[PDB]
Image (tube, rainbow, N blue to C red; front, side):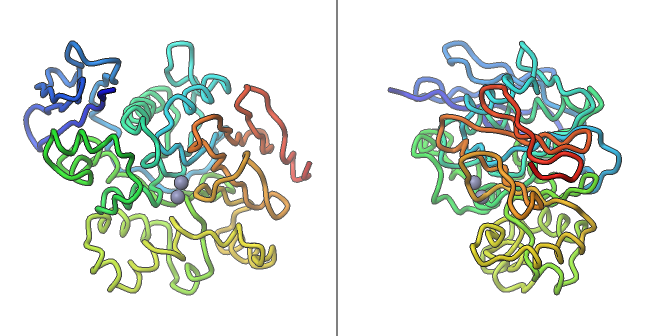
Amino acid sequence: ATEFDGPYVITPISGQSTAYWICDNRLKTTSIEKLQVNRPEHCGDLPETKLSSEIKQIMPDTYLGIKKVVALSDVHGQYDVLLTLLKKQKIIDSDGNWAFGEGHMVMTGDIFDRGHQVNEVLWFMYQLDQQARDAGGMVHLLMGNHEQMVLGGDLRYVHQRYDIATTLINRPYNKLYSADTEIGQWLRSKNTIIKINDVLYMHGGISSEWISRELTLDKANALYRANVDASKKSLKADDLLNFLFFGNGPTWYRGYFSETFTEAELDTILQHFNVNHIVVGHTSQERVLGLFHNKVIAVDSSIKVGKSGELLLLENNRLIRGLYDGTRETLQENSLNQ
Ligand SMILES: [Zn+2]
Ligand SMILES: [Zn+2]
């Protein structure tokens, strides 16, 4: 079985973009006209996208007064599962397009790796970003540890199938998502940690080291954008970058899932950010669930396994689990845990 994969789009600072397509284990290269990334013939059902003049703008990391939010994470290249979940939960319409109005979606990282439909997910999320903006809503795609790994050249977890693209396009996988690329430029605009209303969102979690380093959302998000292309040596040698990018930092920390982590300790973090909840991915669960009297909501629902997933809905002072079958279960209402 040969592959179909792409497109990989190069976007220079002036002038037309170029798209690279893997079609039946051969490369096709097209010149993009009028921002429309159109697939050549004989190329499967690979995604077609209109390039955006707006969604690569860097957006705020803090938001007030947002009526409805949905959160999910760790798709890990499972496009079919993502699409089914969003369809069943009525986040998208019958054409596959944003249907969430002025709502906000927070996807807390880890589109890349393990799965076989990475570019399908990426281009879908790019289109959804634009569509949400056009509706007056937003998609917040946050950087996870696998975004950071891929962009930085840690390729341990890339599906073997992508060796076709790296051979045919003749560059390593990190350079298929470099700053010269449309997707790479889009990703390099993204935040890592955000606050919406009384909720903090990030991929892994916030450890007490954040507090001792006197970090802020803006300072961290800016350093993440500026240094995702730093060498490992440089990241490791800078004390602060080392914190941010590695095991105890926002995109790797798993302390909220440790059997010794205490709710008291969580309370000090909640207080530090003046939030009531922290929503995290990274550490895979069987379902969207709450921990510590629903002060932490885990939204890695194991989409990576390729069978099902779930989301979290925050609306009307409720926390709601949205199941893969389209049903809903309340986790918390007003402040009362269910
Ligand atoms: Zn993950
Ligand atoms: Zn992760």
